[PDB]
Length: 84
Length: 95
Image (cartoon, rainbow over all chains, first blue to last red; front, side, top):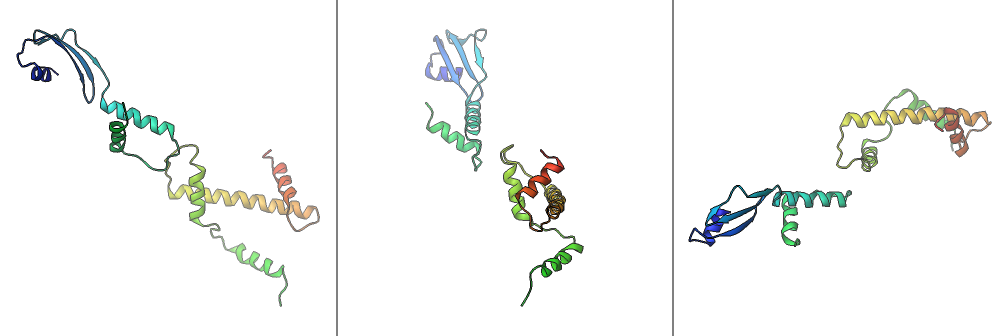
C-alpha cells in the first residue's frame, strides 16, 4: 500500500489516506509527510477469497438439490462479472 | 394343455431349496441412492451396506408374506388382498 502511495506521490513527503483491498485483508493506513503512521492503521479480516467463499456458500444454501458441482474458478468468474 | 396351480407349486419347490439373491443389484441400489438424497446430499456408500440392505428387506418381505398367507387361509381363502396385509400389519404391531 505504501509502495503504491509512493508510486502515485513520488516526492515522498506528501500527506494522504491509503485504502487497500487485498486478497485476504483490507487495510486503512494514514500517511503523514510521506511516513506511514502505523500506530493508527487498522485491518479488517476480509478479502476477495472470503468474498468468493461467501458467494459459494450462498449458492450452496440457495439451491440444495443442484445436480452439478461448481468449482472455485467458476464462482470467481461469477464474482468478477456480475457483482457491484 | 396345462393346468394352473401345479406349476405354481413346482417352482415353489424350485425356489425353495435354492437360497439365491432375488432382486437385482442395480435398481435397488439406485432406489437406496435416491431415498438417502433428501436427508444428506452427496452421500456415497459401499457394496457391503447395500447387500446388508438387500438381506434385511428380503427378510422383512418374507416374514410378512407367509404371515399374510396364514391370514389369507384363516379366512378360508387362497388369494391375498389389501385387508390381509393391513391385518398382518396390525397383528404384528407396527401401528
